Length: 162
Image 1 (cartoon, rainbow, N blue to C red):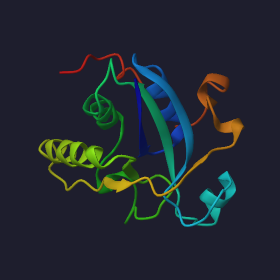
Image 2 (cartoon, rainbow, N blue to C red):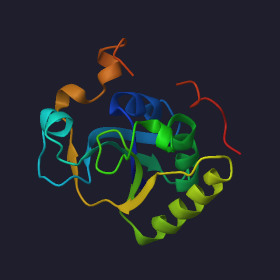
Image 3 (cartoon, helix red, strand yellow):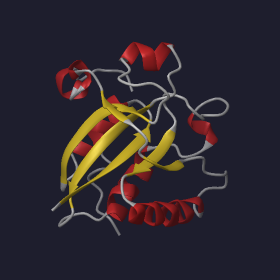
Image 4 (cartoon, rainbow, N blue to C red):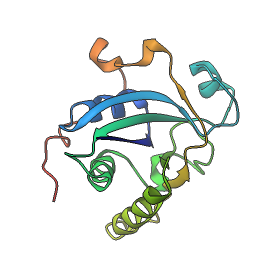
């Protein structure tokens, strides 16, 4: 029926809005994943270096989209290279990553990253790790762009897949 995948690719306000417009995506929940603390607030993540990455929990209809499809959509809007931000993204708020909750997904993600690397001259730095921890962002952050259309940080979601 449904499957979930966790994606970190920058400000979750934009990523969330992007995925909820895709046909087949059932829900997109903004949150904080794979950090070193429990139940962090936006302030903790942004200022206290808790290690969490702004992440979107994407739930999709397995009858409409495959995990591979979701990943291709992901690669269309994320910067999977070191150019995503200055220096090492390890443990940073806007780092790129795909966090799995099933052992089978790890191979799908690995192969997908390998294929994506084929189209990049620079090395990809996207993390492929299990979902260590995930904490829902404050309610104020959910559907942020639907409530605040001019928020800082689109049509790639309309383009059909291979």
